[PDB]
Amino acid sequence: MEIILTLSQGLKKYYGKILRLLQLTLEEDTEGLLEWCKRNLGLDCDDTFFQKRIEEFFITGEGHFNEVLQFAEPFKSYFAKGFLSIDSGYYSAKCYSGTSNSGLQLINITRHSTRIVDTPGPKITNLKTINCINLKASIFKEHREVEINVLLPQVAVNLSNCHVVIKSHVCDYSLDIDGAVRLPHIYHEGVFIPGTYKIVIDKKNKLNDRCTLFTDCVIKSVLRQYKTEIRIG
Amino acid sequence: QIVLSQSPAILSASPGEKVTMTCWASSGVSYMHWYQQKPGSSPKPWIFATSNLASGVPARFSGSGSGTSYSLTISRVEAEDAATYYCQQWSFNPLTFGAGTKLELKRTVAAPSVFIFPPSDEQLKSGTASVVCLLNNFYPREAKVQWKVDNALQSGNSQESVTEQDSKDSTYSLSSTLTLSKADYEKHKVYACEVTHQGLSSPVTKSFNRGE
Amino acid sequence: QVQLKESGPGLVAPSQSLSITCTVSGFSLTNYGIHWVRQPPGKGLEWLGVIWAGGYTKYNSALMSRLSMSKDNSKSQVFLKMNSLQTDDTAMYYCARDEVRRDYYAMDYWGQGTSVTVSSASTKGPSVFPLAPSGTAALGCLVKDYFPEPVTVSWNSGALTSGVHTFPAVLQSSGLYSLSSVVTVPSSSLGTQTYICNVNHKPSNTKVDKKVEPK
Ligand SMILES: *[C@@H]1O[C@H](CO)[C@@H](O[C@@H]2O[C@H](CO)[C@@H](O)[C@H](O)[C@H]2NC(C)=O)[C@H](O)[C@H]1NC(C)=O
Ligand SMILES: *[C@@H]1O[C@H](CO)[C@@H](O)[C@H](O)[C@H]1NC(C)=O
Ligand SMILES: [Cl-]
Ligand SMILES: [Cl-]
Ligand SMILES: [Cl-]
Ligand SMILES: [Cl-]
Ligand SMILES: [Cl-]
Ligand SMILES: [Cl-]
Ligand SMILES: [Co+2]
């Protein structure tokens, strides 16, 4: 009484595992996935296999790639469009192959980070006058949008009552939950995350009217920081 | 396992009629395959994934369904459609098939042509006598064939075999074989098979005299 | 064209194992899985298992203790082996090609099937006797006392098919099978046209041609 996943159904679960390993999602549905892989890929898609697929798609892979991140039978049509819609049916991310990027667009967070010491500073920071070196903001009044460019992604940015789109050279995706901005994590002899990313806040709706950012305001050399809050809505 | 129950077991239809056969699954499945099988041949893919006709399948066929209930419909039946149709699910391991719906074609009554065959001299030399009565190309399938040896009705020493329905004219054929030892065969003179069938206005007897 | 052909032993003893081969052409086993399906006499179809293009297997859990499958890509052959054989393993065995679509799998090409009888009885070849014809005449061949099923019967090397009726075999009280094959022909042709039945019982390696003529 084992369920049989069709080609399409299993691909969604295959992507769902990748999204969980990337840490963009916290849950996964893998019922029937292993048989789907043995049948349609001719291999065991265990954790080592998936880690190699992720490493290759985002970093080491070169040439055309297929829908299952490999570089009659399915998955023999290798793309050159630069991205895959990693789409589980429960969540989705538009993810760009490392070959489509002008070099490496990631940072190795396994290396010891330059430690940042606490320092007194305003609990509120204005969106129009950000002194924090980890964040840069652009307001587009014409289209009622705010873009926050996060330049030190290792410093957590927590969203409160926000509905945003994350743009990066790694993946683009939407976030509708409170808490620290989730970022793709790629294992390649260590943990890697995007080197920068953009938070896009649309204010042309009402649901961002209370959107607020909480982060460490990093200032300079020796690095210093203090808790601050940036109201967007 | 998913149990597939096909109903009815036998569909009898005249040419031109619309017929529907049902495949009920013990639990819901996402699609249903159908296969056609004629006697002596392998199952032939007929409908893929509930409603997609396999290449070469006539447009008079269609499939439909969902969940626990699927069907195959023939909009206007034709003689060549006589066959057994199996459903099959691919949603759960193990893959399972229904036991089949046998479509039987009706036609106007056709009387059998009756032939009788004495034992061959070669078989007699080896000690056994087989007498064969042949009923050829008849409908309906029901028929009574009794053996008379010297006008004595025989019991328990004959066996019948019936062909499957003909795909072109929807008829059947039947053999009845009387088996006797050489000595018993040589004890009597008149060997007759008497045939009763709906297409005959009275029973027809074919006979021969041994050695004559 | 895509083709599949099963080959196996027509008779196997209950103590032995059953080995059957599926030889394919018109496609590569590196790209297509192969299923085995069986059909006991007068009974419905039962899926046995599959060997996928990549070599991994999946068996019916009701018989995975006794069934195994393998393949030889270079020979275009897939193999079935079944052990601990029981009488109810008597069936026609088919291989069928696996097909993958986005929203379903299918079994899109089937072999002709190979017959397997599981019994401790010995093979026996048939005796072939003429059923002599005596506007339409009937003649035939009696194919008697053989084991196991099946026999193939043709007429005139398979050139004569119109009017042929080869009857399902009957099980005699001796445990041996018997059938007749008959054909109707124009009586005007009986003096000039020749009619020969060709009988093949592979389990006993019996091949017989018997000319049937009026007495
Ligand atoms: C990511 O950073 C880690 C930590 O700096 C690197 O791990 C080091 O790798 C070197 C080279 O083999 C070793 O000599 C060190 O002992 C490692 N240190 C630790 C703490 O693991 C890792 O190599 C980096 N990955 C990449 C791809 O550059
Ligand atoms: C944001 O969330 C992270 C993770 O829960 C936490 O460590 C941090 O203190 C929070 N606040 C700020 C200002 O980053
Ligand atoms: Cl799914
Ligand atoms: Cl989705
Ligand atoms: Cl099942
Ligand atoms: Cl219903
Ligand atoms: Cl191929
Ligand atoms: Cl298995
Ligand atoms: Co003779």
Image (cartoon, grey):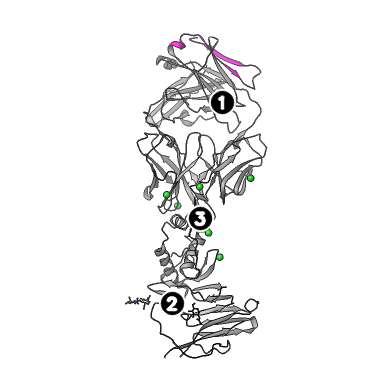
Q: How many C-alpha atoms fall within 10 Å of the one at disc 3: few (<14), some, or many (≥20)?
A: many
Between A2 and A102, the one lying in front of the other is A2
Q: Which residue type carries mark 3?
A: Leu
Q: Is residue C86 above or below residue A73?
A: above
Which segment is the magenta one?
A: B183-212
Q: Secondary structure at mark 2?
A: loop
Q: Which residue type carries mark 2?
A: Leu
Picture coordinates of residue B109, whole percent (x, y): 65, 26
Picture coordinates of residue B19, whole percent (x, y): 65, 39
Question: Which of the labelled discs sits on residue A104, or is there none?
Answer: 2
Q: Chain of mark 1?
A: B
Query: Left or right: where does residue A15 sit relative to residue A46?
Result: right
Quadrant for residue A105, please give it.
Answer: bottom left
N-term mark: 3 or 2: 3
Q: Is residue B144 magenta?
A: no
Q: Which residue type carries mark 1?
A: Ser
Q: Secondary structure at mark 1?
A: strand
For the question of whether residue A36 can be seen, the reply is yes
Q: Is residue A45 above or below residue A225?
A: above
Task: Tell me the distance, in whole angstroms, between the alpha carbons under discs 1 and 3.
Answer: 47 Å
Task: Tell me the distance, in whole angstroms, between the alpha carbons under discs 2 and 1.
Answer: 79 Å
Evaluate whether label 2 is on the same chain as label 1: no
Q: Which residue is mark 3?
A: A5
Between C65 and C165, the one lying in front of the other is C65
Task: Tell me the distance, in whole angstroms, between the alpha carbons under discs 3 and 2.
Answer: 36 Å
Q: Is residue B210 above or below residue B25?
A: above
